[PDB]
Length: 243
Length: 9
Image (cartoon, rainbow over all chains, first blue to last red; front, side, top):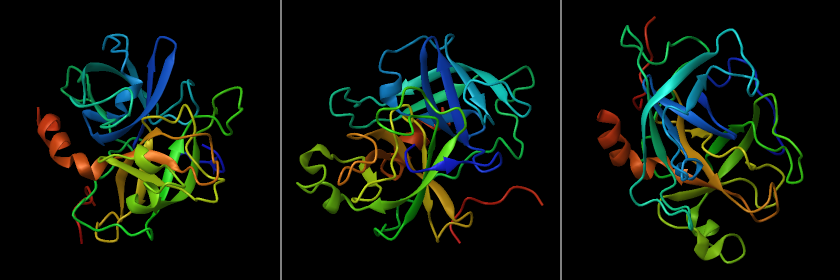
């Protein structure tokens, strides 16, 4: 994340860290046994046994005291996902339950994030938070150690699909957030991570409305980050989550 | 206490 600061330990209980082989991705706990991430992180289709999910983590790849490590029972990429356009860039991870039949062991540092309403009409007005362990700048040598978070405004599709910004590239199922003047954005290694935005309707007032997907550069002017519109896939999430 | 609803208010 560029233009962001370190996030406090209790700030992000829903964020998930995904490890396998030499790769890394983030994700969001949407239910005690379910993690929502980006499909392009798994386009290589690595075996589930290889996969490791760590919840309640603050420092990337560091063991910690409320850290919980879980195996992945199975995962599902969206059927219509394109590795070229990154359309439908979302995937479900089914966590492996233990002997007690529990997956995630909920605590103040490990909690699921509320799914979005979707029925609400989002103005540019909506403010969001983006989080990740990715690069802090485009040229950055290494991923961040501490979790970085940044405040970004939601951006309308009509403005987004504009020629000046992203133009034709934006497709249904996609949403944008950030400042056209740039400065604050998601960055490579942030993929799969959460975009939590304000929902005044909701009782929790904050819902997962985006999955970090793609973009051009970090924080470049007129090039806001592109996310998967979680609200667009509620039926799909309901359908395969229920499994 | 208990869990807090994710439902719209």
